[PDB]
Image (cartoon, rainbow, N blue to C red; front, top):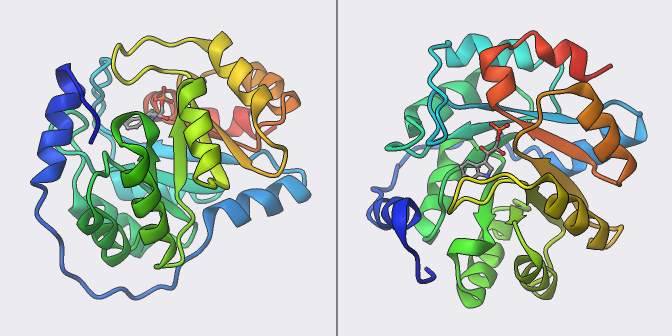
Length: 247
Ligand SMILES: O=P(O)(O)OC[C@@H](O)[C@@H](O)c1c[nH]c2ccccc12
């Protein structure tokens, strides 16, 4: 991984020693980026609903993962499930139970730094994974991207700044997540996010991430060319909001 400080250094160390999960995979892969594209074609707002019990920025909600997922399944283009254990209170068991209960695409959200984690995602039932440019070196990112693709997954590659985007573009990313929140400082910057979105090639599927709680923010982002929206906190606090968001 890259030189890291603070909580990011810690979570990455936890990931390096994350035990692998052995399981047989039942359902074939359902492409999330292709489903986003077809929702775009049919003019339906594409929301990736995220499930997370806790977050380092303060979230702490008790809500049944299965019921939440089955409800979101009626509206969402896909689901994002946190499997990071220490800061997000996620687990592989949760991803496994959800994957067996819904039939929409599932993105496994964690801090992926080694190939076994992608093996875990595949064996657990996930359809794709998140790769974060800011914690990986360019060689690592390229290997992991190639590795995810060998399972037929197109990973969501997350950028937070211009240097992240140069790397993402250089390694041939086709599915990019623009995170308005800096993982290191936990600071949100809507403006920097807008600038980055505007620099991205039109043929890349773009997913806006973090801090979205209002339908107008979605409408604005959509006019900037964003294809999908990853929403977690506002939906965990109020699942019903999904009905306002897809109008
Ligand atoms: O809850 P929010 O503000 O809607 O944010 C969602 C999500 O995109 C944010 O969870 C996040 C973005 N990238 C990550 C990578 C790891 C863990 C968490 C994240």
